Image 1 (cartoon, rainbow, N blue to C red):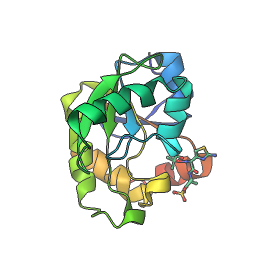
Image 2 (image 1 turned 135 degrees about the vertical axis):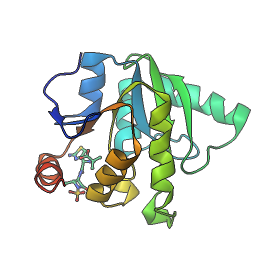
Image 3 (image 1 turned 90 degrees about the vertical axis):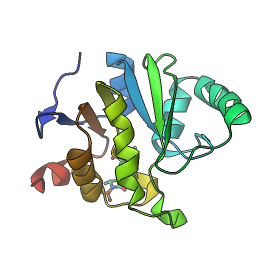
Image 4 (image 1 turned 120 degrees about the vertical axis):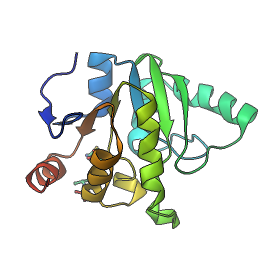
Length: 165
Ligand SMILES: C[C@@H]1[C@@H](NC(=O)/C(=N/OC(C)(C)C(=O)O)c2csc(N)n2)C(=O)N1S(=O)(=O)O
């Protein structure tokens, strides 16, 4: 299903791509959302994935929170993938701009290990305020299942690749 990815390790793949467009095209078993603990999908990856579901992800998420309460930072829940995927794994990476502990990034990535294959963004990057080069390192040192990383920004993609150890 997936095409055009650079192989970084035995199990981590990366591509310069819009995760929304990739989800729509591939319809993978699991797409990862870069969520917050309230599953309020306002901006960033979450805002874009939600908009691609015509707000159906937000409606489902509102029901989830009403029933179960908020996630923990570093935690996850599995919901519908709607039109993008079979399932959406909503994962909460720490938001450095809210002062959340960057050490929880490894816990966040550990959620990915419950799924054999996933399409995902770099956790805690973008508006979550962490260094994406750090995030990718934590990814490669934590995830053991097959992860296809979609990086929207071409300059960031190039830097992630060119700096990868
Ligand atoms: C240059 C990238 C920029 N990334 C983005 O803004 C990028 N958003 O998010 C992430 C998740 C990082 C991505 O590119 O996958 C995006 C989505 S739609 C658009 N026009 N740009 C960001 O703060 N950096 S930095 O290299 O980590 O400074």
